[PDB]
Image 1 (tube, rainbow, N blue to C red):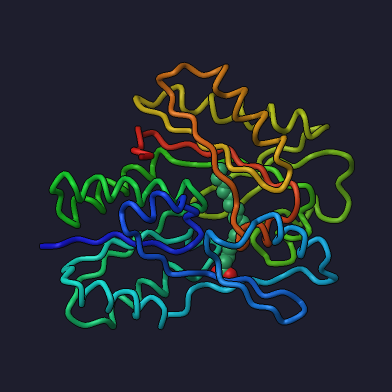
Image 2 (cartoon, rainbow, N blue to C red; image 1 turned 90 degrees about the vertical axis):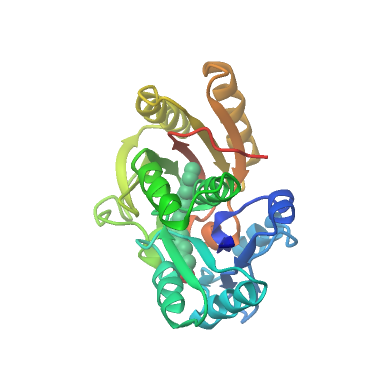
Length: 288
Ligand SMILES: CCCCCCCCCCCCCCCC(=O)O
């Protein structure tokens, strides 16, 4: 038995980890209203994506990995000698990437594919990749890994804010918000993931209080966990995520793992400007 672990590009793992563990990536892409197509990777500067999105008369659209892209990656790993492939996918509630990796795994010959629906995104999704790799090193078998990740998913989540719901509304990736649309006010929505989908949680008066609300909601949850990893995932307003990251390092005990990451182009296209998430995993994920 020889187990590989791969993922899609929305796991947003650092290039250091991708290089170290030779993590294969099925890339998602963004298409701008001028017809320019960009596949996600770590070489394109995220600041230039936000600049182009801001200069777009029409919101850019995104594409999941084609089923052929999953198949090609599966065949490449199989031909390297891997007998089993664990695949960590973007939430099935917001993208068809998972079901396409699942169906691609049915179609590829000569290798066993174990597709996993992370029901989240960004480095929180990436944490499932890092847990699977760690377990492969420890000699666990594919079903044992899938079982462990499924348990991990029960104590994993995220809350988030965005400047403007228009991007999420345009793509249909905000669930059950046909009420705070258009109207709202200077008030700020706080959203959360729930069974793979993005739903409203609370409406607060200011953005400053929304960021305080992110921390309170998450700390209230993880105080009951035996292990805790927290991820501040920042959008285009650098000072928002850096301030929350710094504050969490101060307010939390060192027994909490507190890490930082950012949104890539595909997720940023759906969030728009001002995205800021606070995610948690009830595990001590190996980040090295
Ligand atoms: C702290 C963690 C926060 C995570 C927030 C992630 C927000 C995701 C918003 C929707 C993204 C949808 C991508 C769809 C890609 C496609 O299939 O075209």
